[PDB]
Image (tube, rainbow, N blue to C red):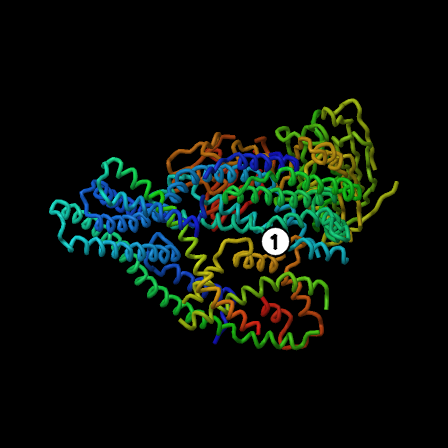
Amino acid sequence: DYFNGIYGFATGIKDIMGMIFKTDTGGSNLTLDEILKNQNLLNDISGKLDGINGDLGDLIAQGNLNSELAKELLKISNEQNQMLNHVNAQLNAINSTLNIYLPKITSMLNEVMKQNHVLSLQIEFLSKQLQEISDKLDLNVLINSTLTEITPAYQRIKYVNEKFDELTSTVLNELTELAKSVTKNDMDSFEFYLQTFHDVMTGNNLFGRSALKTASELITKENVTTRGSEIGKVYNFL
Amino acid sequence: DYFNGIYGFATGIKDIMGMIFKTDTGGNLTLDEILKNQNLLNDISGKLDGINGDLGDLIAQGNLNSELAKELLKISNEQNQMLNHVNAQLNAINSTLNIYLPKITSMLNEVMKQNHVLSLQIEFLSKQLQEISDKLDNVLINSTLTEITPAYQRIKYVNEKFDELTSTVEKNPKSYQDNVTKEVIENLNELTELAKSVTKNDMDSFEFYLQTFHDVMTGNNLFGRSALKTASELITKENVTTRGSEIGKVYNFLIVLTSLQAKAFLTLTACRKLLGLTDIDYTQIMNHHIDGQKREFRINILPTLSNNFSNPSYSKNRGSDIDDPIVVLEAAPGYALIGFEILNDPLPILKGYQARLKPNYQVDRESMSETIYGDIHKLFCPKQLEQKYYIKDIEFPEGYVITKIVFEKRLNQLGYEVTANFYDPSTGSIDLNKVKVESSDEYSIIKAETDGIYMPLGVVSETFLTPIYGFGLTVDNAAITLTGKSYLRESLLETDLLNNETYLIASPDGYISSIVENWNITSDNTGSWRANNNNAFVDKAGSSSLYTHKDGEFSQFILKPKTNYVIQYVIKGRPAIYLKNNKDTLFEDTKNNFSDFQTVTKKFNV
Amino acid sequence: NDISGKLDGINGDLGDLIAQGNLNSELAKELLKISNEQNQMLNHVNAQLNAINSTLNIYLPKITSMLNEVMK
């Protein structure tokens, strides 16, 4: 087929992002963590209120007790039932929101994996056209320096990409855990590695050595006798 | 607008730290409480309470079989456990909304405000430091890269992310209770999470990176190679240059890096308050660290650096062989020459800045002016015949500031004469009677190429605008170089390398004056600009902007006859700009369409 | 275990007194409020003591034998 360029890849991505951004799940003001936390809290209060109203109910229906008192106990049984009813209200809403959500999500993950497979084919050609280069390589300090500077960020991004692909091609906890790690606000975040990757790529990094610059050198090292021109090989890397 | 030095930045920070340090958040939270659950819990609590209330009253009104009174009590405990456990959650939520959020949102609000003020004072310098790395390609060098980049990346990231989050947290604590949005809560969580990470005592701590940053900066690092020392090296061995002197460039670096840690410490202070840990006054340590970087700069690097500065670019231009031009840059009585810029966009132009001096070679912002000289290509370059260039490195003695430079080109023989007056750093008065004069025997001559000669181009100034005591023209490549000698050293040592008040102006990027009044729109008031309809209004595009729609127009009344002026404006969209006389049009710009803001530069002229 | 043991038998005795009636209304209330305070505290203590007893009783046995085997 045609390869539709970086602009092409990047728009293809933007599209899938949009598709995700426009998926309407249960539009609950609260997170996923807050729904499963609240589900457990309410499920427990419901569980306990049931067995209390159970016990209080058995006491009333064992009779043998004053009329006037049997009334007050009944009024206390109604209040208790109203409260269990009002609780199961909350817990129904939570359980039906989850019943909307997982269906909306599993189909959206499914679609993402599909639309992503289509894009990964448009660049499949070039794992084999880049392998052709490393085979024919054999050393600066300027080269070694940008390896040490980038590989941290490269490894995790690659890892998180591949592991996300592997987990969606088989659908859910394993996925929500990776999700939790990718989105956690701490100094050593995914976003941090994603940013420093770009900083290294463009040379916004104190000394101002872009990796593009350093990669370019290695490719134009006059030992590299593989097909294509310097332009091609570098643009491949890019 | 004045940059108040490192001392200035660092005390600005110390102040904000104090403001945080004196915030009270008295009283028990994880900060993992679902604040959205307030209504849910309040309701369950409300109902459970009144039932346990009624059942309680029944027990304590006696009249009740013993065996039964037991079972009812066991049913009261079950109920009470549950009410206790609920009110736990609901207390935490009510205190977070009621005590905590109010004291926190006002403190974060203030920090964001006082931090915006500091970030402006060094905004100039992300663009003046980027200018350097663009124009850049030992073991001692490689070693401080390996030593610092880990710490640099973490500090920078955590600083930027903390700033981005504190500016977009909701500051109205009312906004957090009752109808709070996923978005309002997510900003607060994102902040408390980053807080938890910034303050966590482990081998990969923020404090650890903040310490090793300083250790590398001062050369407490086995080898004893300071980063200032290495950063100095790279800059002095520059094959193609940027504006300013070695001193300026290095002191720029010094500012960026101190500023970074300054805010590292502020971020740290902030995060500890958010998490309600015991207060640490980082101020003492922060100041010790920043002070050491200064002394290391003042003692070990500074005295090796040049205060020379030159035109950073060149330009191929053809001049006149048949013109005998005189060009005179003369400051007014009380004023001194501060710097120049050759540019060629409208035409070959030499811009000259002047101003009145403050003590210790600083400049008086308000007293500051510029003048444009035209066709300097006829001064600097010949066209078909060789040009002789008398070369002399004119230098005056300490305490003298250059107040006039004259260029004379006669029969393709260019010369210059410099005048300097005595200046007193204590008062910052220039003495108009104590003048010295030098001019340009020893020369260099460039032969004219058909194509042109490389005339100087770009801003000839110090990084921070400062009066000058040397000046000269050099020739090569058929290339002409203007060089001057700044007083930046003498100015840094009285003011900022001593922790005294410091008043530095940064070399302007463009024009700083206009004959147009209220040429820079910022507020809604447009002063001298008059609108006509509600079709014409001020749009807040970050930096504000005149806006027109349908027929909406803005006008301003004004020039000497038969002279050339330069018009430049920064425009977006599809406007029409006129200099109309109610009969003639003197200048027109329609037919220009832009997606975004550009700058447009033209000239105009009985 | 000790705090639990003591709190239990007091709340036990105070509980029996309330449920044997014969008690002024206003007073029977205050004694109930003093039973809740006591019960909260006993509940909160038995929380800790349950965790401790299950760690020692279920968990440690199954874990120490599993770690033991793994080491071997």
Vertical relation: A231 (above or below) C21: below
Quarter the N terminus of chain B occupies = top right
For this rendering, which residue is in front, B606 or B66? B66
Give the residue drawn at x 42%, y 65%.
A173
What percent of the width, then of the height, locates residue B418? Answer: 78, 33
Q: Residue furthest top?
A: B433
Q: Is residue B132 left or right of residue B165?
A: right
Q: Amino acid at mark 1?
A: Gln
Q: Is residue A238 left or right of residue C8?
A: right
Observer able to see residue B276: yes
Q: Residue furthest right?
A: B441
Quarter the C terminus of chain B occupies = top right
Q: Which residue is mark 1?
A: B153
Q: For residue A156, which quarter of the picture? A: bottom right
For this rendering, which residue is in front, B302 or B331? B302
What percent of the width, then of the height, locates residue B50? Answer: 25, 43
Q: Chain of mark 1?
A: B
For this rendering, which residue is in front, B477 or C13? C13
Q: For residue B303, which quarter of the picture? A: top right
Q: In what element is the residue under mark 1?
A: helix
Q: For residue A61, which quarter of the picture? A: bottom left
Observer able to see residue B341: no
What crowding class fits label 1: few (fewer than 14 Cα within 10 Å), some (14-19), or many (20 or more)?
some
Number of numbered discs on residues: 1
What percent of the width, then of the height, locates residue A188? Answer: 55, 56
What percent of the width, then of the height, locates residue A62? Answer: 16, 55
Q: Is residue A219 left or right of residue B84?
A: right
